[PDB]
Image 1: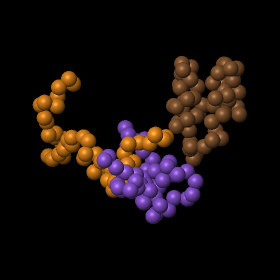
Image 2 (image 1 turned 90 degrees about the vertical axis):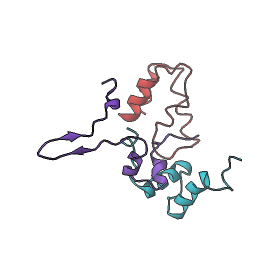
Image 3 (image 1 turned 180 degrees about the horizontal axis):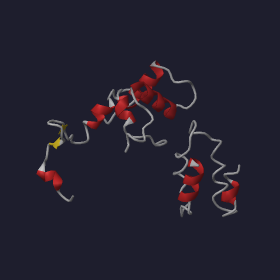
Image 4 (image 1 turned 120 degrees about the vertical axis):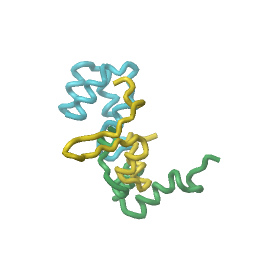
Length: 50
Length: 57
Length: 50
């Protein structure tokens, strides 16, 4: 019960890099750049309410 | 900027004088027994103008 | 957003920031900044959920 700090500082205090932190809460989306264009790993269920 | 805008915009007027709020929204080394009286002195009593006497100090 | 408002970038700065938040006074070192954080949630003599 003291002053507030960003709750990612304890994660870094547990030896977690920023990239690792990002791969612990969110689902990643991979894009490919082939044939001079932009593709996407589409997931139909994710397109809910957009 | 930071301290002034946050303090003024928030405390309007925080109703029950929510002390346990902006004291964390302040810099430097915390948990002092010095900065305390400088906040319980401004909020009420000489309202409106006192909030203009705070930043200038 | 939490990462966006996070000053620290690694483990050292994190442990040091926590050390300065908990014990604001003496200059944060290596042993102190680490041992303090360890004796908060990772030591039986300083933490116990029974």
